[PDB]
Amino acid sequence: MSDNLTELSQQLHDASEKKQLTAIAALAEMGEGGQGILLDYLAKNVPLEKPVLAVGNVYQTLRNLEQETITTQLQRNYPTGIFPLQSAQGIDYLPLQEALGSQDFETADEITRDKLCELAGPGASQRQWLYFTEVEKFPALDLHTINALWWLHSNGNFGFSVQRRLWLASGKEFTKLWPKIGWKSGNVWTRWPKGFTWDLSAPQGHLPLLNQLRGVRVAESLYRHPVWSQYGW
Ligand SMILES: C=CC1=C(C)/C(=C/c2[nH]c(/C=C3N=C(/C=C4\NC(=O)C(C)=C4C=C)C(C)=C\3CCC(=O)O)c(CCC(=O)O)c2C)NC1=O
């Protein structure tokens, strides 16, 4: 509370992402004055056009206070969250957003799987799992919405985009990817659901899950999908 609100506000409004993040964390611990600065920043930046990590971090930091008035104000002003909930198939992404805004990552993971089957159409909806060719033909827009929500509500630590970047970093070697994202530990495949880490202590890329029971083809088709380069992920 001895921190300088004028200077922290300026740090948030400057263009350095790394300095924005430290300012946001400090401001959120500075009562009405700091929280008011954060609320004004949201008001000036929402709805997003492109995903902006700092804006997601402001929203989620404020939600995570779990204080009545701020929660009420965020829900009234941003009833669908901070990012347009767009779909090439008219799908409803609000339940996914709500789970993510509550930091209920396990529910969000379950919803994401249901939505991908819905997106793939009647065959996938009935069998409740995907073929790699269905993934290849997903519309980019829906994948962008889904990924943006995961990324914005996890400080950039979750999302298929995050997994893709780690997969590229590993030379596209899936056997190196699994330990990096916590899906295998040496010889031990992480058991679903109890072995997974349903919070932000999880490794980067841990969520959303892609079951490996039917092999890696779905994951590879997802990571190679044109959406990522199209939207700058
Ligand atoms: C490679 C070993 C591996 C095994 C033995 C495995 C088994 C497995 N995973 C399941 C579900 C599931 N398993 C996962 C995810 C995982 N589960 C894991 O063991 C791992 C490593 C992940 C990776 C994220 C998910 C999300 C489900 C529920 C969705 C689905 O049934 O596809 C089921 C239940 C299928 C059913 O009831 O119809 C089995 C038998 N999955 C695997 O990937």
Image (cartoon, grey):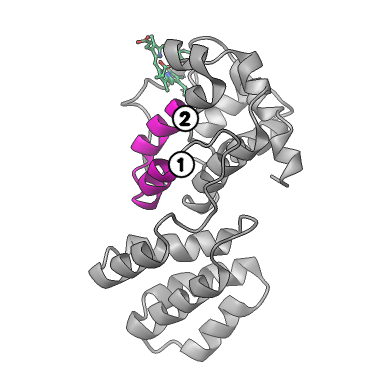
Give the camera-side residue of 11 and 73. 73
Q: Residue at x 46, y 81 (%)?
A: 37
Disc 2 Cβ-to-ligand 1 distance below 8 Å: no
Q: Quadrant of residue 176?
A: top right
* Disc 2: which residue: 115
Q: Quadrant of residue 220?
A: top right
Residue 157: tell me if it is visible: no
Disc 1 Cβ-to-ligand 1 distance below 8 Å: no
Query: Is 53 inside the magenta-drawn segment?
Result: no
Indicate the secondary structure of the residue bearing disc 2: helix
* In the displayed structure image, the side of residue 172 where residue 199 appears, left or right: left
The correct choice, above or below, for 84 with respect to 204 in the image is: below
In the rendered image, residue 216, in percent from the top left (x then y), is placed at: 60, 15
Q: CA distance from mark 1 to mark 2?
A: 8 Å
Nearest to N terminus: mark 1 or mark 2 = 1
Ligand 1 placement by image quarter: top left
**Mainly helix, strand or loop, the magenta region?**
helix
Residue furthest toward the left?
68
Q: Residue at x 57, y 39 (%)?
A: 87
Query: Is 114 inside the magenta-drawn segment?
Result: yes
Give the camera-side residue of 224 and 144. 144
* Disc 1: which residue: 93
The correct choice, above or below, for 32 with respect to 197 in the image is: below
Residue 167: tell me if it is visible: yes
The correct choice, above or below, for 216 with respect to 15 in the image is: above
Q: Which residues are magenta?
A: 94-115
Q: Residue at x 50, y 73 (%)?
A: 43
Q: Amino acid at mark 1?
A: Tyr
Give the camera-side residue of 161 and 197. 161
